Image (cartoon, rainbow over all chains, first blue to last red; front, side, top):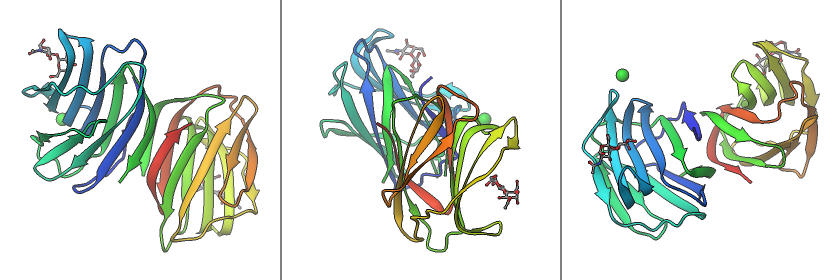
Length: 133
Length: 132
Ligand SMILES: CC(=O)N[C@@H]1[C@@H](O)[C@H](O[C@@H]2O[C@H](CO)[C@H](O)[C@H](O)[C@H]2O)[C@@H](CO)O[C@@H]1O
Ligand SMILES: CC(=O)N[C@@H]1[C@@H](O)[C@H](O[C@@H]2O[C@H](CO)[C@H](O)[C@H](O)[C@H]2O)[C@@H](CO)O[C@@H]1O
Ligand SMILES: [Cl-]
């Protein structure tokens, strides 16, 4: 729906900075990181209003097409109709997600993927920049 | 280095790509188009490849077929360095802005109104991609 990027070969130790514009009417947006569309080490989905969630961040994994156990975050530094930046650090055991306000939290790497080769965006978000750091 | 689709780049926008050119570089390329078989722009600076030495080769690809090459003298590129290129387009041409200030045009052969595919490859490592 939004950007799909493959042929990446991000490895442990490297950082992704993603800046985007959140829609005025945003309901939800997501960032998928993984091997391919069925093997996601990280599905990051801030829900403004969707699936029954309100101002909640839902994080999950996807293994061979099937979703894992959700993990919710109540930290919610996102405003509809804004331009935000999120940074994801890929470590061996887990991922660190750094929010626009500085807040950080971790998510485990349940796949035990050694690299990130796929990135996708969806929902109510317009990718503006992707950086490798 | 990267294969991207659903880019939906439109006229009026500027695509900015910044990356580092390898120490022992032979070539690097940026492809823009519909898909891998249908490119409105293959931008390939060759430090030394296919017989070409310090030359910028540009072309199109229509249904898998390369089109007529266009060669540029300007070669504001040094190996081992970090470069940035800015591409914008319209119905008739693609404008490519290089480091030295340098800039040229390339015809919009397929007359695409939106660019959905971008690939980046060769002796170049992508540091950032922006849509301004
Ligand atoms: C509280 C609770 O259990 N809610 C869930 C939803 O989160 C879930 O929605 C799916 O969530 C996955 C992430 O795990 C993807 O975001 C997918 O897009 C969502 O639809 C649904 C269905 O799986 O189940 C409960 O409603
Ligand atoms: C002088 C000359 O005509 N040389 C050409 C090549 O440049 C060309 O190589 C391909 O060129 C396309 C651009 O047209 C891409 O850069 C592709 O990667 C290159 O292989 C070849 C092959 O089509 O034809 C002549 O040699
Ligand atoms: Cl699979």
